[PDB]
């Protein structure tokens, strides 16, 4: 009779990247169908989120990135403190881009070429001679990855990792791009940036000279043909407090089987960027996705409810 989640309050966490709200609320909706009372997501620093999940102050995140959060995940307790099954979002991507105009003009294919100060200066926006890379907010996993790579690739003398508010800085980068000036930035999918700056039209991805990621000395991001963009095909997982998942088998099953296409998050994130980014707007996007994928969503719910619970 009673749904398994009756009377149990769930506390989602995500970052203050509101482009994460859609996927987070999708999990919340499915949890509601299991009977849980789900609070609005807490938007917190990623590491605070991980420590909160480990202590039980939070229930789940839907934005556990591989490889970007590997080091935070392990440092916060790893598999001893967290439940993590399945893959919520497959086929995410990351890397460094420059505008296609400058890439084609100067035959720039690899970030190693920015070791030449004459090339790096093309991307200098503040007059100090160094290329200005639009990069990651303090505390993002991509902060560590970029800093690691700029050192490994002997780029710190010619490249500055510009940090602050990435979203705001990318508005400035796109505005500069539209002036026809050279730009240099890191981005990921899913996010709104790739809708505004498209590889093969506006920008190109740069390769890297060899694999290098923080915390994994044996990382290998090379494609079978020897190409290397610096990052693997990336994923997001649902991560839950381990004890909570053990006490909530229907929710644990749900977390293991949910999957959301990266294209759908990309599309939602673009709609936000285009002007529909309110809490109510995003709730509507979640409800529209469910309607368009109702059999699949219902299947998650029904398999979860059928767990040994």
Image: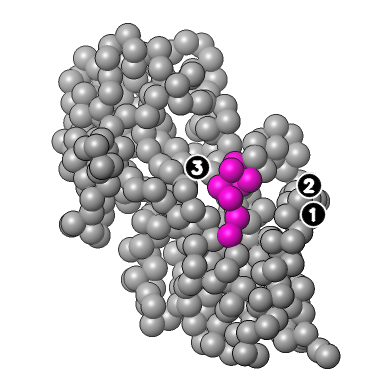
Q: Which residues are magenta?
A: 259-266
Q: Is residue 98 above or below residue 7?
A: above
Identify the mark at residue 189; answer none if there is no mark: 3
Q: Is residue 269 above or below residue 171?
A: below
Give the CA distance from mark 2 to mark 3. Answer: 21 Å
The image quadrant that residue 70 belongs to is bottom left
Residue at the extreme right of the image, as rendered: 1
Q: Which residue bears the numbered disc 2?
A: 281
Give the mark, 2 or 3, whose residue is nearer the N terminus: 3
Give the mark, 1 or 3, whose residue is nearer the N terminus: 3
Q: Which of the two marks, 1 or 3, is nearer to us in this view?
A: 1
- Numbered disc 1: secondary structure: helix
Identify the mark at residue 291; answer none if there is no mark: 1
The image quadrant that residue 158 belongs to is top left
Residue under the image location 54 percent in, 33 percent down: 193
- Numbered disc 2: secondary structure: helix
Q: Nearer the viewer, residue 186 or 301?
A: 301
Residue 225 percent coordinates (x, y):
24, 37
């Amino acid at each position: 009779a009673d749904l398994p989640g009756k009377g149990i309050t769930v506390n989602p966490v995500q970052s203050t990247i509101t482009e994460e709200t859609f996927q987070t609320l999708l999990v919340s909706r499915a949890l509601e169908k299991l009977g849980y009372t789900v609070n609005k997501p807490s938007e917190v620093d990623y590491n605070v989120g991980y420590t909160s999940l480990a202590s039980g102050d939070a229930t789940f995140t839907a934005v556990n990135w591989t490889p970007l959060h590997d080091n935070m995940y392990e440092a916060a307790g790893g598999d001893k403190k967290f439940y993590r099954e399945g893959v919520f979002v497959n086929g995410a991507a990351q890397g460094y881009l420059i505008d296609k105009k400058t890439a084609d003009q100067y035959k720039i294919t690899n970030i190693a070429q920015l070791k030449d100060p004459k090339i790096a200066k093309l991307f200098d926006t503040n007059g100090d001679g160094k290329a200005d890379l639009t990069g990651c907010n303090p505390g993002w996993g991509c902060e560590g990855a970029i800093n690691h790579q700029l050192a490994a690739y002997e780029l710190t003398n010619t490249v500055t990792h510009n940090q602050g508010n990435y979203a705001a800085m990318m508005a400035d980068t796109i505005s500069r791009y539209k002036e026809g000036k050279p730009v240099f930035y890191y981005t990921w999918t899913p996010y709104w940036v790739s809708n505004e700056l498209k590889p093969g039209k506006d920008v190109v991805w740069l390769q890297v000279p060899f694999s290098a990621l923080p915390g994994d000395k044996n990382a290998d991001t090379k494609l079978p043909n020897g190409a290397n963009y610096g990052f693997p095909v990336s994923t997001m997982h649902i991560v839950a407090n381990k004890a909570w998942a053990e006490k909530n088998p229907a929710a644990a099953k749900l977390f293991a089987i949910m999957q959301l296409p990266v294209a759908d998050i990309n599309a939602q994130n673009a709609i936000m960027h285009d002007g529909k980014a309110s809490e109510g707007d995003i709730q509507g996007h979640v409800d529209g996705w469910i309607k368009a994928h109702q059999q699949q969503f219902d299947g998650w719910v029904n398999e979860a409810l059928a767990a040994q619970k």
